[PDB]
Amino acid sequence: LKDVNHIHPLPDFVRGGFDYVPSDIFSGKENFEQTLRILLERLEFIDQKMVELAELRTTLNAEDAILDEIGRQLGIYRNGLNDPEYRAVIMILTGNNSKSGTRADIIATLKQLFGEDGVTTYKGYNYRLDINIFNTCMEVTDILPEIIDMLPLVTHLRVVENQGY
Amino acid sequence: FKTPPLPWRNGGSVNEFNQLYSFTDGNTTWWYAPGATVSNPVVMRDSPINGKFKVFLD
Amino acid sequence: RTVVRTFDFELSGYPDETFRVVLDSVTYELRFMWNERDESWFMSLGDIGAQRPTITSKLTCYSDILAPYRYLDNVPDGNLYLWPLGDIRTRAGRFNIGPLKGIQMTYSSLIE
Amino acid sequence: NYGLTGSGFNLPPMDDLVQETKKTFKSAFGEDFNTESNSVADKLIQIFNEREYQLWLLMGSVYYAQTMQGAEGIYLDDLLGKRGIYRLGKTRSTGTVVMTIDSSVPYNMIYSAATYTIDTDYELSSDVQVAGNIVAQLIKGTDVGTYRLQIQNTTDQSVKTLSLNLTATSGQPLITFFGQIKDFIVNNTILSNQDRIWIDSTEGALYIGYDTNKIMIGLSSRVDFRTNPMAGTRSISMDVRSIEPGYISRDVHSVRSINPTPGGFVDIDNLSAFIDGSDVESDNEYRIRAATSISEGKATRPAILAALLNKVEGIEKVRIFNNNTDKTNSLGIPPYRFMVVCYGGGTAEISQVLYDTIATSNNTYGDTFYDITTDQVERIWHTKAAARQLAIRVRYRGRPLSLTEETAIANGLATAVNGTMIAGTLYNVRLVGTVMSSTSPDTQVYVDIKNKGQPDSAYVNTDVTASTTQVLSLELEDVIFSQI
Amino acid sequence: QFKDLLLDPLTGDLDFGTPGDRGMRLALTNQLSLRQRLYLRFAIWAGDWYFDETFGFPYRTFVGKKTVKAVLDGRIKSEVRQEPDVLQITDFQSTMDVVSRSYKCFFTVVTAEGEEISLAFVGEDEYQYPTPPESNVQLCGDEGVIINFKNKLYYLINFRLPK
């Protein structure tokens, strides 16, 4: 019924405070109101930017200019990656820390990179595993090094990518 | 039997082995359940045509 | 790290409570401030008569408050937690802190 | 003082800000400036001041958003997202139910999955067939003629048949007929089943999958079994899930109805608490799950060993073997496939547990298989150990043991049922110790062991070892005593 | 706001509920709680409940004796005000019949209603924790941003043409 995240712009900030004019003594004088409005409306701008200072620092929306700072703390350097996929690698490596490389587990990680039906996985008798891609939205060669990391120590892997079925 | 027939009810539970319950759809038939007791009641379902219930003979 | 429960807290709901407590035979002073917009309790910890508090943090349920601060000579080495007595989904409030109000703020000390 | 300090972020009250700004105004226009109550400047300054209180509070809230404590809502995910843990969404309750069916319902009839609802919010998990899902049976009173009995072996896959005649409808002949049926069933499945079937001679009825108090507790696993004259009342086990995801819970004996009543229906009830569904995951249990992730082990030999023993309604024993060098090795195994041996774990339920295996580890060897949907569907393999019963003879010198005093000794040899697959060695010295332990203290004692059915010449003292897929077994009635 | 097991006003037994929702209920509204708090307070004769000799009403003083109507009304009207959440008593029609020797009074009591302080012990929660995203929506965008824009364009094309 209520949002748990209380960090939001204050609703109707301006009309508040004006509500503290005692008994409409000054209201309708058009000389005191403008002086008060001009000062209060400055806080509006500062109040608004208080959110982006917290909202924009999250990894989901962080821009490349500062996303590097988030990656730097985790040891994931930009190298030659671009912004749209640099976000992906950060998620992939971080998610690897609570993984076991099971068949059900592997499907889950690939799920975040290719939608619901964009990926499928065949399995083979002698350590063979196969990955199929149908709806890639980013160039895969640069993402490939991580795709190896979350697999068992002895996996034998093939990678094939195509658009659609 | 006990003479006064009683109406069927989907939310009813029977506990008496000798009373007649008048089911209707106005096709009225009278039903009983010998294996009904206070210790082992039975639930009047949507329809009696589906166990322990038996229809009165005509 | 065996630990034993040894102290419990209660709050009257006044927005600027301040009182002195004794833990592990040492004495500390605590300050609690209520935040309106964030509807949460702010806790400050320090030595008796200290110019400034040593530690300030925001209270939350099932979070180890002292975790990153067990490296100072004036900080308790025990465990401080807030967990609910009722439904597990209830979050810390203003008047719902106490041994029977819904949230059990507790301190426990390691066995040495 | 109240901003950023060496010990975190603080909060200023309103009055301190009011006094500070009033002092600033005083300095602006000398000590004579009025700033209390009646001043227009007072009404402007006080109104102006309260707003920055909100700004300070919000700023203080922002700072803790990036700390182990104080994170909430969306911001909480980022903090714990660094450690690869994500909230759980809406969930659907899962569980199993049983129902008794009238004697007349044919075996081959199959219930349509999409034409029934257990109760206001439960439906069949999938299609269900009566055959192969019998869990308990009750036979009583009304049943002369010729009867056929069928059963699928739980280790092999060969159907077995038995022929009998019910020349009498009561008395010792009926008791013998029931005993013959009991012997027929116990020789297959698992010995634990025999503990849960008996005959109430006082009433001349046979109970399958009940307890001494006449409560249906079920057999050790779903099975198939038939009688050409379909007598008694049969019970089956179904799998049930909720309609829409959310929060819902049911107790051990809650489910009580089915809306569209199928012909021949008798009753329906629960056996154990359902895995209740949940709403959107909250912060508290999110932190709790983040804290207890240490024990979450998978895809390792100790992990797979532990998981099986704690996720199956049975699985008394388990053992694994490895062959990973270019060849089939002595034991018949493909070059790069694991081997798993279990006891009393069923087929489908245990198969689902095997999804903890390391990805790309082929495994998949054994005598029995099953298919599981991931989406794609894949097949897994395993085997069930073939029990081998022993015959034990005890000879001693001393006072004659009295009847009902041999019960302790007989049950004492229950340790013989605790041998492990392959690596099971009796160590007859251990048996001598046990037989001399489960009794009052106090001359001579010996133990002889042989396979069932062999002549008396087969008795020996050397220890016995289980085969590759065999496991030791023993029955109470297969113990004898001799005085010397 | 005193919580307690709900007593049926019509029968006096516990209010297990209607046949469609049979169960157990707690007295939540202040009105229901006060009703039973007065009912029990008046129904238990003074001294007849063990474990508390001081509880109850002393009917034996008046019943069976020649008594003055005015004295009885004072005691009846006084026991009511022992509850800490009684605002006032509106009217009081005390009448006595000498033929049948019966006495019967009427009156009503006014009580306000309070808040619940905390919902931790009762049923539900008031927060709206977020829902995790689905599939590759987070890392690649969402289609709804296209659907809403298309709908806005269509409705704007609809607006300009007079109708």
Image (spheres, rainbow, N blue to C red):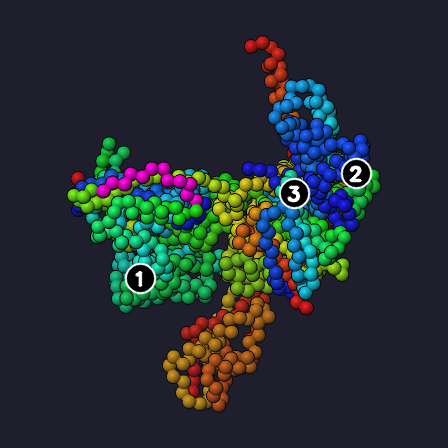
Which residue lies at the image location 49% right of the left edge and 57% below the top edge? D157
Which chain letter goes with mark 2? Answer: A
Circle number at residue D149: none
Neighbor class of circle 3 (other Cα within 10 Å; few <14, some 14-19, many 20+) is some
The reply to whether residue E47 is in sight is yes
Which residue lies at the image location 50% right of the left edge and 67% below the top edge? D387
Numbered range of the magenta stretch: E85-96
Q: Are marks 2 and 1 in contact (CB under 8 Å)?
A: no
Which residue lies at the image location 65% right of the left edge and 58% below the top edge? C21
Which chain letter goes with mark 1? Answer: D
Question: Quick one: quadrant of the C terminus of chain C?
Answer: bottom right
- The verdict on a common chain for dots 1 and 3 is no
- Which residue is tagged 1? D205
- Which residue is tagged 2? A66
- Which residue is tagged 3? C35
Which chain letter goes with mark 3? Answer: C
The answer for how far apart the CA atoms under marks 1 and 3 are is 73 Å
Per the image, label 3 sits on a secondary structure element best described as strand
Magenta span: predominant SS is strand
